[PDB]
Image (tube, rainbow, N blue to C red; front, side, top):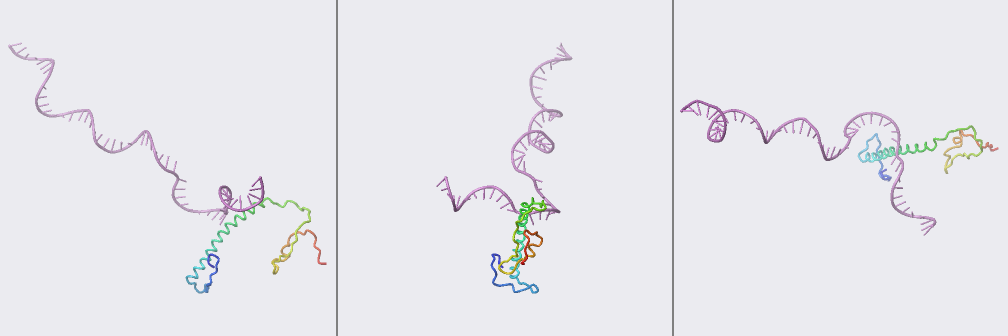
Length: 105
DNA sequence: GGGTATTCGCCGCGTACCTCTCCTAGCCCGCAAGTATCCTATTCCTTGCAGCGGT
């Protein structure tokens, strides 16, 4: 793909066991430089993201034994239109129940 | 007045480490050093006044 998001109509028809000629290598070079610059900027930003996050939740500390309530949320497997992207057994593994479940009996 | 749009200005943008260099400008006044000049001698000549033999 060329810099501005377009896809070149002529692909690179040469692997690395054989040799890339000049132009093919040029295009690959552009792609690699885009990747490198993106990693640099992306990590720079992610650092700021995490620093913001840890400074809004730093004061929270589990500090009791049981609040004694009954409200929860309905955990269900996630569906996107297609298959199950995440089953139920991996979304409630290790979270206490709110209202005892009744089997489908 | 009043609800709205548009503009202006402030706030923010990763961690840790290693190597190197450079850090005010300009005036001014004492002051050391180096020098050209001015007064200091010697040798020649021609005057002006005080002693002084001589009679």
